[PDB]
Image (tube, rainbow, N blue to C red):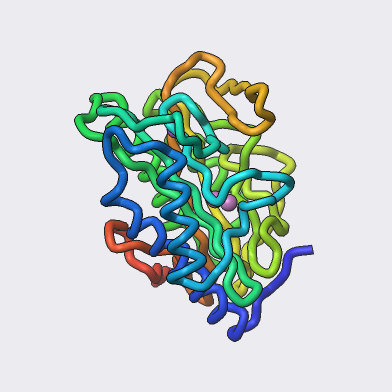
Length: 264
Ligand SMILES: [Co+2]
Ligand SMILES: [Co+2]
Ligand code: NA
């Protein structure tokens, strides 16, 4: 079932989350034209291991071969870091990180724009981030997860993009992927009432084009069927007594760490 974390668990999650966000703040500078995805994966790994003294949860997860997922342009998710894949001007890149510290996990990701941006690229990252923020703003005890999925979808579609169906956010803590499944669209099957103490991620994958995807020969890389661009953002949060607390907040986030719902 869904696990309610205790205050102490939360404190642990706060540490794992901060570490995860840090990695994202740390790698920004190195994200530029000409750099390979493999080198970025190496930098993150070393940082996590040697500086943070933590562990990457992705490395070996169901056989995942690298430390972080780096998805470029049309890649939807699970892009495999590789030394032959170089960053170019105009690319939109997602870097997804999961760190373990003391047994608790912190999962987060962001988009980066390489060099000069395209109108659509920049626009797609912005609506994708807005769609995550919107969801975050909704979280409070008593709401149903279905309303969140519905809201994201409606928003995204009203802006002319699509939400990927196959991939969802998830409960998280001692376990990388715990209940519940957090769908980013409306589904009559969804029925979970939020309680304080619940910890989970929200990580909408948005396509500028059609919602369909395809998985490559590699068994990991997922791409849009129509070759359109795809973007995603993700945060880890805890449901509080009157709202939520964002455990993976970074300095460039423009949403506050704690969201209090005065209507409560
Ligand atoms: Co996740
Ligand atoms: Co992630
Ligand atoms: Na992408």
